[PDB]
Image (tube, rainbow over all chains, first blue to last red; front, side):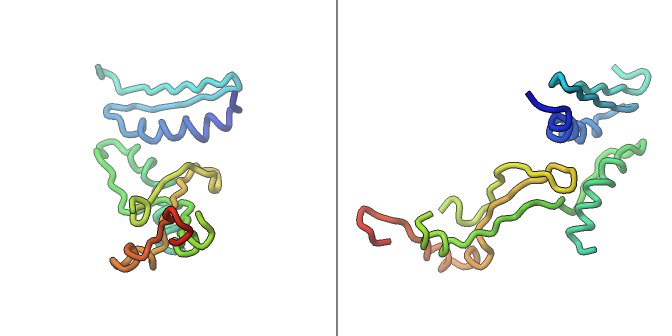
Length: 49
Length: 50
Length: 49
């Protein structure tokens, strides 16, 4: 029941700030739509379990 | 810019981007971001029954 | 006694596009000496404080 902005300001960035600290990380990205779901993908460097 | 402004900027735009550098293990910021502070006076509270 | 010295975090607010904490704490002048804490008043059964 929330707009994309609300889920981006209150959920995506908060979770992303900690996600930035994981080991062996190549990059991270996040996406939010009007459907009410936020999806974050974290790609790690080659050879990481 | 005062100390609070510098610390807020460091937390907002530096700490996260400074940990994107390879080899950076831990980042410890000796500062805090801005916040809304409500400094309450108990004497004034009791005078209103709150 | 519990809310006379420490800080209390309630919720977040939007400051210039970022979620920032809201903290309610007693004024500094009223949390410095034992006299300040010992001057706190509560209502009893009677109207007196």
